[PDB]
Length: 371
Ligand SMILES: OC[C@H]1O[C@H](O[C@H]2[C@H](O)[C@@H](O)[C@H](O)O[C@@H]2CO)[C@H](O)[C@@H](O)[C@@H]1O
Image 1 (cartoon, rainbow, N blue to C red):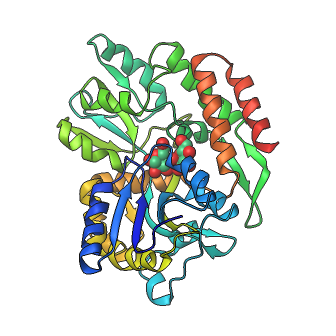
Image 2 (image 1 turned 120 degrees about the horizontal axis):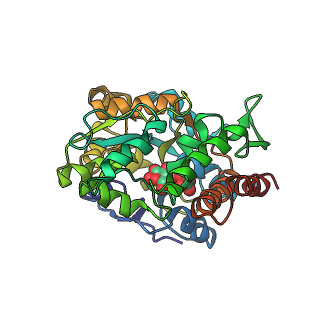
């Protein structure tokens, strides 16, 4: 189920899990408890799978959109900070982790996608999606490409689909209408079609994934990429000269990334929910704990902790991150977010490889989600 006397932590691989072990150590030092940190693949899926059979990690880290689902199947545990603690953190971040009024996780940081470009290849980044194909033309005649980003994860294609009107679930009367989905509206269709046109006019590859795009950009073979703050760490090492800026517009409207709040929740069956409360409120959610994690891999634009946020809000990458977040939308945490991601993942993939037209693909997805 767990062990008792120890703390198992699960974090995704793209995150500062090493800086997280460091806080772990200081914890174990000050305390005496063994703190293990793992980062299994498909963590988001694996969790409930195990958390269910009464076992798994003590603490689970994921963006908040998955938390409502977990809370629903009962795998989480209600947390209980007090006006002392809660006040250290920005209000809207606490709101991101409330499932039916209740707090089911601790908010760490706001994540938003940004346009990352090679200042060597491109000193001036495009202002619009529309000029990318042309840019690619006169980059391709040099064994280079204009852009590559992960097309295998809907999170990365969402900003474009959402720019002209696509939407997940309509928000009405302080609640999401689960039957009013905008994955198959005019806006969503226009965004995807454009994407598909990029592929079909050989400006992009239907297969590009996280690794391929990371490598491509880090190696200097692509002028631009789309990713979050976690990625800066690795780019700092490739030593490519890069800027981080606002995603390009689509049909004159801003790209609208789905904004995630990195959060930490405690397993329903963690025998040491006490140890967990200690480590999360006392060691990690501190200027010192956040600095440890951040130095490993950038946390994001805005951190939940108001005082730490007092120092990291000056960087031009952080700033662009805050700009894109601003134009974006905080994700819902409702349990149906999982069906949404699954249906959308299939749609883009099917449309992009040509097994389905944009129309068939998005209709399928819309059906799947409201069924
Ligand atoms: O691609 C759908 C998934 O999108 C988000 O996942 C993000 C996550 O928020 C981010 O912190 C981690 O870096 O990148 C993944 C994208 O691969 C949602 O949080 C997931 O629930 C969705 O499945």
